[PDB]
Image 1 (cartoon, each protein chain N blue to C red):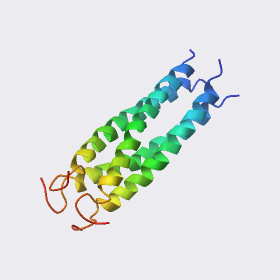
Image 2 (cartoon, chains in turn blue, red, cyan, yellow):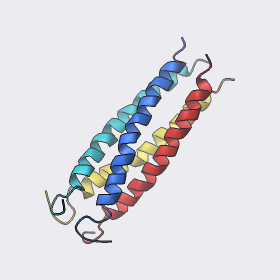
Image 3 (cartoon, rainbow over the protein chains, first blue to last red):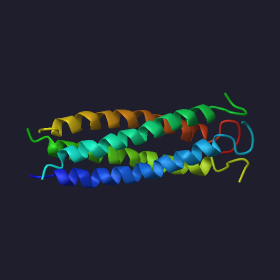
Image 4 (cartoon, rainbow over the protein chains, first blue to last red):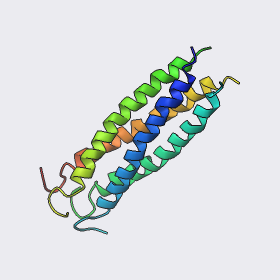
Amino acid sequence: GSTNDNITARLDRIDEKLSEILGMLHTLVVASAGPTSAR
Amino acid sequence: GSTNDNITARLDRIDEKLSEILGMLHTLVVASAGPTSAR
Amino acid sequence: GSTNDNITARLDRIDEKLSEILGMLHTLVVASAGPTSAR
Amino acid sequence: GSTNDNITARLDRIDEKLSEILGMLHTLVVASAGPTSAR
């Protein structure tokens, strides 16, 4: 039936997931930006 | 009730999020491609 | 008509996808944390 | 009204997006795995 709130409920989880990814690539863009060399 | 536009409204946010991720891994695929060495 | 379960069905796939990404950036945050140098 | 197909239509785009991310971190997990050093 009304699974429409169910979507909003797991998509809110997907956003929670990218909230990890985002910060982790932010972290990677920092590390990969050059941790021991490069500019 | 009609949360269906609400989904479209936060999924548009998820896409906004990967628009960061995408470009940031693009950045990582560039950096990790070899910033100070490698090919 | 009722594509609402269809969304939940492909969004469950998107979550399955980030379950790869998440762990892979976890992996990257580890590797990029310094595999041969850096801290 | 029925934005429900609209969701499926942009979520199909989000999946298209992670299809980039997934492969790009795959790429990063490869590069970050050690391109010039490490194991």
